[PDB]
Amino acid sequence: YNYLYRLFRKSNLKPFERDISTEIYQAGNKPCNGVAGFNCYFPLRSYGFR
Amino acid sequence: GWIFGTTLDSKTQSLLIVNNATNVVIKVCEFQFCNDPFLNCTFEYVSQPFLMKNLREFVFKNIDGYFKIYSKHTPIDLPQGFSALEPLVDLPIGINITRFQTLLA
Ligand SMILES: *[C@@H]1O[C@H](CO)[C@@H](O[C@@H]2O[C@H](CO)[C@@H](O)[C@H](O)[C@H]2NC(C)=O)[C@H](O)[C@H]1NC(C)=O
Ligand SMILES: *[C@@H]1O[C@H](CO)[C@@H](O)[C@H](O)[C@H]1NC(C)=O
């Protein structure tokens, strides 16, 4: 679980751009306010290498 | 000096360029910003100052993760003449820049 990848983002990534910011993704209408829930997901998901 | 960034609130990386008549200091890491100086960090650059009636023109652009800076100091309001600008630097910053501000004394 030491490796993570970005799953959710508002827009596409420009070439050679690093996006290290970590804010809860807004996939719905109500704001997440730092709480993961319905239509509110953590963007970084961990690889499950086995 | 100048500051560039998206939100400029220590949530995303923000370019900072400072002149002090001795050298140019350029960094990319993030901090909270409030106006001008008085009296986690990835890229650092130290160079020669961009300093010296006299008109100083600069061009900043962000192409493919490269921050390109061109400049020209000329002796002379913008006059009717024509003067080209020579490239100073092409830094590999690689950040998302949408807003900027200037830094006075
Ligand atoms: C750089 O950051 C700005 C600011 O967040 C991004 O502009 C946002 O773009 C998304 C989708 O394109 C919109 O939903 C937001 O409303 C925009 N925000 C603002 C303040 O305009 C911009 O997309 C980012 N650059 C890249 C290449 O992703
Ligand atoms: C940037 O700073 C934050 C908070 O201090 C920290 O969690 C994070 O690991 C830092 N980034 C790197 C690449 O170490």
Image: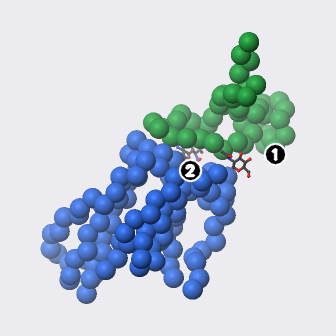
Q: Residue under circle 1?
A: A33
Q: Say whether residue B7 is visible.
A: no
**Relative to B87, is A50 on the left or the right?**
right
Kindly indicate which chain is depicted in green in the rendered structure.
A
Q: Which chain is blue?
A: B
Give the chain of mark 2.
B
Q: Secondary structure at mark 1?
A: loop
| Between B94 and A38, the one nearer to me in the picture | B94
Q: Residue at x 59, y 41 (%)?
A: A19
Q: Position of residue A3 (x, y in %)?
A: 69, 27
Q: Position of residue B15 (x, y in %)?
A: 52, 58
Left or right: where B97 falls relative to B33: left
Which residue does the numbered mark 2 point to in the structure image? B42
In the displayed structure, B16 sits above or below A25; it is below
Residue A34 in sight from this viewpoint: yes
* Residue B78 on image: x %, y %: 25, 77
Whether residue A15 sits left or right of residue B7 in the image: it is left
Name the kind of residue labelled 2 in the image.
Answer: Thr
> In the rendered image of this protein, does residue B82 appear above or below residue B29?
below
Task: Please tell me which residue is depicted at 52% across the width and 47% down the height of the picture.
Answer: B96
Q: Are marks 1 and 2 on the same chain?
A: no
Snapshot quadrant of residue B53: bottom left
